[PDB]
Image (cartoon, coloured by chain):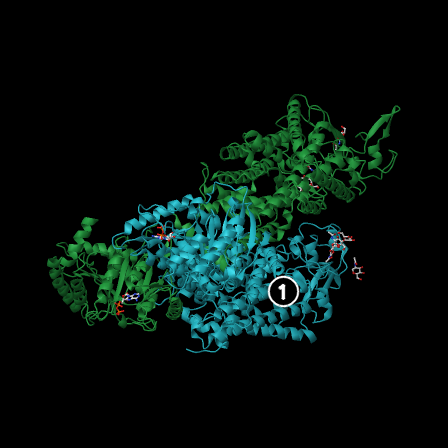
Chain colours: A green, B cyan
């Protein structure tokens, strides 16, 4: 299967756009509203269709295009929810379009072709004949689809012959127009059907005698009477030509709006008329305005003539290269249609009188097609041409709606219409054709183009709005599988299309638009619920699971680094031998530092064997959940059963979360009684966990002396948090006290920034820097710099220099002494502090100097009531 | 601090509801719309407010009540997004209410109290309104700036004025019933003349023993002589009557003014039911008939009258100083609503039944001698209602001017919206500083319209937006079972709040659809902006933060509730085994998982890497990228976990039991087959396989062991001829039947024939068929003989080493003679032994059982599978 762009995309879209709306209701629309407002309407109705076509192309290019049709692409590229929603609005639009074309064919048959074989009598004739035609067309569609697909070329040929004849007639009008006298009464419009000739008196047998017009206007058959209406005798009777040759005075004439009312009379603005009363037996003698005309009504009546851009991408499977052949073809069809309407609007407006355009049924002329009056060969070619075009459009719509319904039914998206997929032995639908025919009858029972057209418009506008909105949303949030290759495509275009087509959908009828939107929302949510129930198993719980998975998948792609740094903690609790939380203050501290917003996972390892201790794990999980609910901290809880607690801690540290929902901080407690007991396990386990959390580039929070930390009911009134930032990790060391004081427990503790990084430098510049940095934070904490020394900070400087370059025992003995001098300073100037935060030095590289490192950490925090040590990970930015 | 229900909630709400609409625009509404439609209007405007009061009570009952005010409760109980959105609509409503009350005070000053002080003296009335409203707005802002304390002291007086006014109205009516007042209104045929100009309504009067033309004649006929015939035909053709304007209460008037009489702009107020002979008229007479001022309809009347019943959120405004709020707020608010509704109903009926249908339609009381139309019936004098309404309007304006900037200051100090942080810079006392100025500017921009009949709909739009948002939030949070939302109200049900949302939305669209669209877009923009700011504050990114927050919210909500699903769908964990060069050994497992899930569900891909964590981080990260790429190729959407353990066996276990977050857990482990276990000299592989098998059966997980993974098809291949074989032996029938269906759901197995072979036979077949009806597979069922002795191994393991092999070899014989040419064979395997040493024999069994079959997949049930 391989065919080019032309015979695969261009000709079908053109054949679907040229409909009956042009002939039957273009001239009337142009004359009633003028040339300006008509051109503006055409432009407004082409822009929405252009933005929808661009979005449709952006959809049709990303990835491969499914070979099924025009509904499979939408579904595959926008999800089952959207695809299901789009298919149904399109189905309803198609069945009402078939109905409307049947109405057009009936109207053209009973009014101009042959009126003998026929207020509300006309409506009843329309109903009866439309029902008969619908029956016959449904039967034909049942038996003879092959012949329709055979004869489909003829309908386009007829349309082209008709348009060629119209333009040829115009070009012949410019230099030699036809003759079609329309009769006048002052500034009124007479129906030429009854009268033989329009003249008050005629000369018969050497003398004047009253004409049929007289006898119809005056009840007296003798001229010598004075009991007639004043308007007839007061004004004249003229015979102006109806087809004035092309000129700039006529296009100047019919240039301003002429919106009439229901029942008014078609009047020729620009003739002398002296008003007077009139009888009530004369109204059947003037031409009358049939329906109330406005701007929104004309929008609604014209819109079904620019629809069908989804009909071009309808033989997608039998295409050579669809990605490059569908969009260009569709847009070329749009451009051709827009230019044909513009040129025809201007030619009609500028070539025909402003009073004969308003005869919806061609009353001024002797019951002819008003647009058929200007046609070179004869007015009989356009009538037959439009008749065959209407029949063909009806047949093709009745062929193409049931196929869409059958596809949607066999896709098993909406469950209650599975039966509509019981196709024939060949695949042709059976109980979808019946539903379509019944809805078409329900539409025919209205029997008026001016009321069927807005419903059709609502369905199509809803479909287009949905396509555009889906495209824009999927582009904004970076949907995982959505990458279009179109060059001139940008989500701003789809947004503008949504706005314009929404404005149209609301101009026609706000309440109808609300009903359509509610139907669409109901079907969308119902599809979503059914999909959730089918993938997972539950309705409500299934919805939540699906939302979670969607969010995680979308978060997967993209740069995995955030411009800011906020602590997301993982609290490593240590369960007792009796399965009790040893330090229930860690949970309290986590709740005070997070305040219930963010991610907080709470892991714990249970020594033993997994094969025989599963119930223990479940019990411990419930226990931790209860204890965690009490302290009011909202988080998940993981429990693993390892053989040795060390490897359990490792597996917990490096594997907790799903993709992007990872922790970036490990808060572990302090080992108490490590030197007291003879078992040296404690400090080696602690140091091993420290080394394992520093090699994964994670932050570290080691709250020392956890038994003295406040509870949530406690409150502090006087006190000041103390920060003792030594060299590095300034960002997190400044971000912690702020997030802490944001809680009511530390609601008003004064912050004091103590800095010890003299390094033979000046504090004046560092004070200005700290203050300006604090200005953005707005903490405004007092900054004081203590007189620091290089030899005093030697322990930290060694590591700092090594870190800068990257960007033992001799040193350790010195480190202990520096640790004790620093401890002396801090305990003499910050003893009475409420909470003290200072950054700790990194663990040694040598696996044996760990005891000295522990002695350093113990002699450093000697005397301080409450001290929290934080170690940076190195990837923190702010 | 402790004060009761009455003086803490009831009276403030009453003071906020009874407003100026009642006096200035009730009679006009009743006369224009009739009695019936008036009752309907009152009912419609009371129902939306009643449902909103019920939802507000449900909010005020869950948990403890914040002591701050009326905005803190909403925030704490509905989240920062909703609470922030509500605050702005309520703020705008309050400032426009200040504007409307000022307009009411100006209108009452220029029309009844003193008409000479009309400086401008059409558009002159509008310009006078503009100037005087500006002067008052300035003066009231300054007063509110300096003297809040005296306002808080004198606030009771305004309520005293309102109550005395209403009591006087009813006293006047009751006096009307048996002895009415006198207020003659003059008539011309069936029109209504303005009684201000004429001295007396009579065509001719007798002066000095003779008749002379009266002032009415000179106004209608410009000639001062009776002997003239150059006047309009309407004056001479019709009569001049003087009907009483206040007929005492009776059933004849309520019978008259009972149907709607919507006029048009410029029409004439006509008394239906009087003799009138029509005739043309001049154009210099229009200044002498009373005229309808604006076009009247039904929707217009709803829009103008809705502000009267607003203010139910002002009752829960001294929340901190309350004795027991949970039992005192709802009952107080609802009693205030009921009292207001009954007062309106009784007053509507009283007006309908006491006043003529022609004097109700003079919006400014022209038929009567420029009096307050409602003041005609009042016992002491019509002077009590005028002064009463003046003081009431000034007091309500003052309190709105006091209560709006305070709310803005609260929102600014809550630090939700960042660009209005400056508005929290209160004075030394707490009185707002740059919030009062902004409020005064908005009030001026509202005054520039200078017409109650045009300001009222804007006020209504904002208040309706607030109520709709409250109701919708309550209903949704009750439906989705948010974790921290449990209301204690007795008569509360999410259907009621939903119905309230529907009704108040209907109102919002009846009044003016376009305004409703603008309000909804403002609300949506602020809602999404608050959500974005919350994301920026918790996580760090705007978009990535939004996604993280959505994920966390979904997981937390899914946490609570029954942890068992009615259905069972496989959620796989594919255990890949990386090579020494960090390449996927069997990339066909990922293909098989993608075929079994079809891209919908959860699929985690774990793998263990032997070594030490301290020195092997980069290898793990590189392997993570490798697995992600290989998984992207096969088109399977899933997450990837890699852990670095010491001994692989141990790492596996930890991978099996800890993967996921809370409720997003796996329930099926698909591991490959150990190849070369007996051929390999070392016995390390089977020792690992058996350990993973034993560990995954003790966690109650299903098990899928695809054997011979090197012959499984890829995605590009297609099958035309073949038949899947299922060999369900004893147990695990549900999942053994659900697997082939989910498999054939993919295009690769799109049309492979399914054959069910099952080791009373009619009863069993009937059961399989009835079960198959729901599934709809309709696959052919073939039941081979069932020997208990042959299957003894499965029965004995569920509920002799030499015998094991004999049964396995007979079963292998049967399967290979009746299913050798099968495409895919699925059969359930027996459980591994409890003894840790018979693993070699167990492996020999498993090897000799599936001997000859090209492709065989073995499934073992977990035991908690339902379908
Ligand atoms: C066709 O002829 C009739 C009668 O001559 C035109 O009637 C229009 O409307 C009324 C009579 O129905 C007259 O207009 C009056 O004009 C004054 C001056 O502004 C205005 O104050 C009145 O309210 C009324 O509009 C007059 O006969 C004529 N007026 C206009 C502006 O057309 C009718 O318009 C004619 N139709 C055409 C010319 O298309
Ligand atoms: C006050 O008197 C005026 C003038 O008489 C009333 O206006 C006109 O009243 C007459 C008599 O009711 C109406 O005539 C009726 O017209 C309708 C069709 O419009 C016809 O079906 C009836 O059989 C009858 O002929 C006339 O329409 C009406 N309006 C005008 C412009 O003449 C006025 O209605 C009286 N007040 C009230 C409250 O009725
Ligand atoms: N079983 C465990 N599970 C999780 N973490 C542990 C465990 N044991 C120790 N830790 C980590 O080390 C700390 C305690 O270590 P250790 O048991 O050596 O001293 P403890 O005072 O006896 O308790 C805990 O706060 C935690 O950080
Ligand atoms: N290092 C590993 N990482 C992940 N999974 C493994 C690992 N080793 C074994 N497995 C799992 O157990 C199965 C048996 O692997 P084993 O190493 O015992 O056999 P092998 O293929 O002969 O080597 C593998 O198919 C895999 O499912
Ligand atoms: C009617 O036509 C006659 C014939 O020319 C003309 O004289 C007369 O003025 C016309 N009347 C009007 C009202 O134009
Ligand atoms: C005016 O009133 C007199 C008083 O009886 C009455 O006779 C006359 O008919 C009235 N005029 C009309 C037009 O009814």
Relative to B659, is A764 on the left or the right? left
Neighbor class of circle 1 (other Cα within 10 Å; few <14, some 14-19, many 20+) is many
Q: Nearer the viewer, residue B559 or B691?
A: B691
Task: Give the residue drawn at x 69%, y 45%.
Answer: A437
* Quadrant in which the C terminus of chain A is drawn: bottom left
Relative to A310, is A389 on the left or the right? right
Q: Nearer the viewer, residue B417 or B185?
A: B417
Provide residue B436's location: percent of width, then percent of height: 41, 61
SS at badge 1: helix
Q: Chain of mark 1?
A: B
The residue carrying mark 1 has its beta carbon less than 8 Å from ligand 2 = no
Q: Name the quadrant containing residue A618.
A: bottom left
Relative to A558, is B113 on the left or the right? right
Provide residue B66's location: percent of width, then percent of height: 42, 70
Q: Quadrant of ligand 5?
A: top right
Q: Name the quadrant containing residue A169.
A: top right
Q: Name the quadrant containing residue A847.
A: bottom left
* Quadrant in which the N terminus of chain A is drawn: top right
Provide residue A317's location: percent of width, then percent of height: 55, 36
Q: Report if residue B307 is visible in the image.
A: yes
Q: Nearer the viewer, residue B187 or B609?
A: B609
Q: Nearer the viewer, residue B30 or A629?
A: A629
Provide residue A669's location: percent of width, then percent of height: 27, 66
Rendered view: A365 above or below B475: above
Q: Which residue, as the protein is rendered here, is positioned at the far top?
A: A175
Q: How many marks?
A: 1
Say which residue label 1 marks: B27
Q: Report if residue A379 is visible in the image.
A: no
């Amino acid at each position: 299967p391989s065919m080019g762009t032309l015979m695969g995309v261009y000709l079908p879209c053109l054949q679907n756009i040229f409909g009956v709306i042009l002939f039957l209701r273009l001239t009337w629309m142009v004359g009633t509203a003028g040339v300006l407002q008509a051109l503006l309407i055409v432009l407004i109705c082409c822009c929405c269709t252009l933005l929808t076509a661009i979005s449709m192309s952006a959809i049709a290019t990303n990835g491969v295009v499914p070979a099924g049709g025009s509904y499979f692409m939408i579904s595959r590229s926008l999800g089952p929810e959207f695809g299901g929603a789009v298919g149904l609005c399109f189905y309803l639009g198609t069945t009402f379009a078939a109905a409307m074309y049947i109405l057009g064919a009936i109207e053209i048959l009973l009014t101009y072709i042959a009126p003998p074989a026929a207020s509300n009598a006309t409506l009843n004739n329309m109903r009866v004949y439309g029902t008969i035609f619908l029956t016959f067309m449904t039967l034909v569609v049942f038996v003879g689809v092959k012949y329709v697909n055979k004869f489909a070329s003829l309908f386009l040929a007829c349309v082209i012959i008709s348009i060629l004849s119209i333009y040829a007639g115009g070009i012949k009008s410019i230099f030699d127009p036809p003759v079609f006298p329309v009769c006048m009464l002052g500034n009124r419009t007479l129906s030429r059907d009854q009268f033989d000739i329009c003249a008050k008196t005629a000369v018969v047998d050497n003398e004047t005698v009253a004409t049929q017009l007289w006898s119809f206007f005056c009840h007296s058959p003798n001229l010598t009477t004075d009991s007639c209406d004043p308007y007839f005798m007061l004004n004249n009777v003229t015979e102006i030509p109806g087809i004035p040759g092309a000129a700039a005075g006529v296009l100047q004439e019919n240039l301003w709006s002429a919106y009439l009312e229901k029942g008014d009379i078609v009047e020729k603005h620009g003739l002398p008329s002296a008003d007077a009363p009139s009888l009530k037996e004369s109204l059947p003698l003037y031409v009358v305005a049939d329906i109330a005309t406005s701007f929104t009504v004309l929008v609604g009546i014209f819109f079904p003539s620019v629809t069908g851009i989804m009909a071009g991408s309808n033989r997608s499977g039998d295409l050579r290269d669809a990605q490059k052949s569908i969009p260009v073809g569709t847009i070329l069809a749009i451009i051709t249609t827009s230019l044909v309407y513009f040129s025809s609007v201007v030619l009609f407006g500028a070539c025909i009188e402003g009073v004969v355009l308003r005869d919806k049924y061609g009353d001024g002329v002797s019951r002819n097609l008003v647009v058929g009056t200007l046609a070179w060969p004869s007015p009989w070619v356009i009538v037959i041409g439009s008749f065959f075009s209407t029949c063909g459009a009806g047949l093709q719509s009745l062929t193409g709606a049931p196929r869409l319904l059958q596809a949607i039914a066999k896709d098993n998206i909406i469950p209650f219409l599975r039966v509509f997929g019981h196709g024939k032995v060949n695949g042709e639908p059976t109980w979808a054709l019946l539903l379509t025919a019944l809805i078409a009858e329900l539409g025919i029972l209205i029997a008026s183009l001016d009321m069927v057209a807005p419903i059709l418009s609502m369905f199509f506008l809803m479909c287009y709005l949905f396509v555009n909105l889906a495209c824009a949303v999927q582009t904004l949030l970076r949907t995982p599988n959505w990458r279009p290759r179109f060059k001139y495509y940008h989500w701003a275009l789809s947004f503008l299309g949504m706005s314009l087509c929404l404005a149209l959908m609301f101009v026609s009828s706000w309440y109808y638009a609300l009903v359509a939107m509610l139907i669409a929302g109901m079907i969308y949510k119902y599809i979503e619920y059914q999909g959730a129930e089918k993938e997972w198993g539950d309705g409500i719980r299934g919805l939540s699971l699906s939302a979670a998975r969607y969010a995680l998948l979308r978060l997967e792609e993209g740069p995995p680094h955030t411009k800011n740094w906020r602590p997301q903690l993982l609290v490593l609790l240590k369960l007792d031998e009796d399965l009790h939380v040893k330090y229930p203050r860690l949970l309290t501290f986590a709740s005070q530092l997070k305040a219930g917003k963010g991610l907080t996972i709470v892991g714990s390892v249970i020594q033993g064997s997994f094969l025989e201790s599963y119930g223990e794990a479940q019990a411990a999980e419930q226990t931790i959940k209860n204890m965690m609910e009490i302290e009011k901290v909202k988080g998940f809880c993981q429990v693993v059963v390892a053989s040795k607690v060390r490897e359990g801690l490792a597996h917990l540290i490096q594997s907790c979360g799903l993709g992007g929902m990872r922790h970036n901080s490990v808060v572990l407690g302090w080992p108490y009684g490590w030197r007291q007991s003879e078992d040296p396990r404690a400090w080696k386990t602690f140091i091993d966990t420290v080394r394992c959390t520093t090699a994964a580039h994670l932050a570290l929070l080691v709250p020392k002396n956890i038994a003295f930390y406040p509870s949530n009911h406690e409150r502090y009134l006087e006190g000041h948090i103390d920060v003792w930032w030594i060299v590095h990790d300034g960002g997190m060391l400044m971000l912690l006290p702020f997030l802490l004081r944001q809680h009511k427990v530390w609601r008003k503790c004064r912050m004091r920034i103590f800095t010890v990084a003299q390094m033979d430098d000046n504090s004046i510049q560092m004070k200005k820097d700290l203050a300006v940095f604090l200005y953005h934070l707005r903490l405004e904490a007092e900054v004081e710099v203590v007189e620091m020394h290089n030899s005093d900070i030697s322990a930290y400087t060694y590591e700092r220099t090594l870190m800068m370059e990257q960007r033992p025992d001799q040193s350790n003995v010195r480190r202990m002494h520096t640790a004790v001098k620093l401890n002396e300073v801090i305990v003499t100037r910050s003893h009475d502090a409420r909470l003290v935060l200072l950054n700790m030095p990194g663990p040694p590289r040598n696996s044996e100097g760990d005891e000295n490192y522990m002695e350093f950490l113990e002699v450093l925090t000697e005397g301080l009531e409450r001290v929290l040590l934080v170690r940076g990970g190195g990837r923190e930015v702010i």
